[PDB]
Image 1 (cartoon, rainbow over the protein chains, first blue to last red):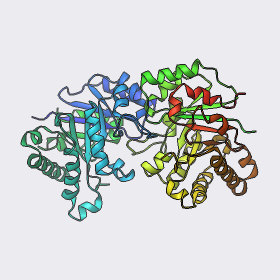
Image 2: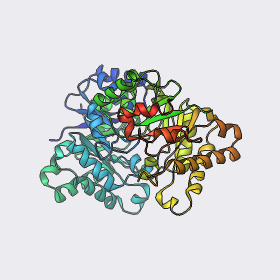
Image 3: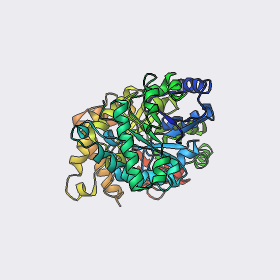
Image 4: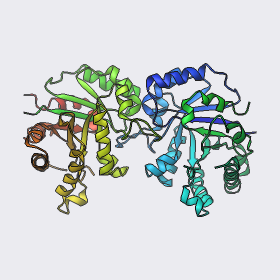
Length: 241
Length: 244
């Protein structure tokens, strides 16, 4: 009874002409109504995308800071994001964690502030290649979700995204991790919450494997990357039709 | 004679409402035309500020990454900045360096990419209180300037800002002048006399309508990189620091 959720993380890609044509494709396509769709564009285009996006696609930012105002050059707040039409924010993404050194406590605080600000959150987790080779997939993923759960009061506003960053994985391997994460939630938070929380597959998703990955009982959607910039994103959204 | 340059770094402040007021103030203010003015707003408002800002104020971003495109969630590039009306980018700011651990080589690569992309750069340097009270204000400021100079081939596109981080955590006009002076000498001997002669070096310490006038008269201080005051009406008076 979990609503399939598909997010598109454009990452550091996009211009006014390229974003516009992606939006036209979205609002001009037959999208499965049952699906909750989200796209995350670069901060400079937030207000712009919101004007071109159909009401069936919610707008997300790719990151934000843990406070509303401050001497933090280069940082944006949940307040600015909402001010520009955004409703979601991606927090804890593997690139922020590994390339930009964002630690669990910081991510924890960002999630807490984002939520009290009225923003929904896609909280990301994932282990590195070395973590997996050392049977540390669970130790890493549990510790990361722990810091997230600790900052979530209303789970109806967050979606978890699992990133097999170690894969730079099979539908079977992804289902296993999603399964364990849900189990962690069920025993450490509540059965109620574990049943309703969407866990998106943040691995490599394309038109060729979306239907199989989506059928997995514990996979409730995707956090798409490169393909979210292509027409192929429409097929990925319609994975469960 | 170097052209006085005043930058306004709003940092993490601003809403469509608040930003509209500041632009209207600048648009309706009486600004010394000799001054080159720049304001750095949060990335979400770039396109918005450009349409409300008078042609006398240039638009800047508060940061950017080192590549045009890529798998770097949360990062923006010089290309997007320019696509939204921006002409400048602040790089190496004390907050990025210390709060977000941005290091010298990374800042160096950003500066080189921003420049080749057609963007002007305000490159920041500054030592911590630990470095100062330890007698290494120079060794820190020189390392940073070194990594900056190494990635600059057209100095006409760059402005350097000095941040007495060691105080922004009180610093007199005398000590500020001494640092700008050493930095300029570093450039004169390690880059060229010409470049050191023309490069603007802004004071990024705390600037207000109360000190801007005497800080500006310092021979080696060519402007400011204002913080909190750039959100208030006094920013106008700071821009007019050298007026008569």
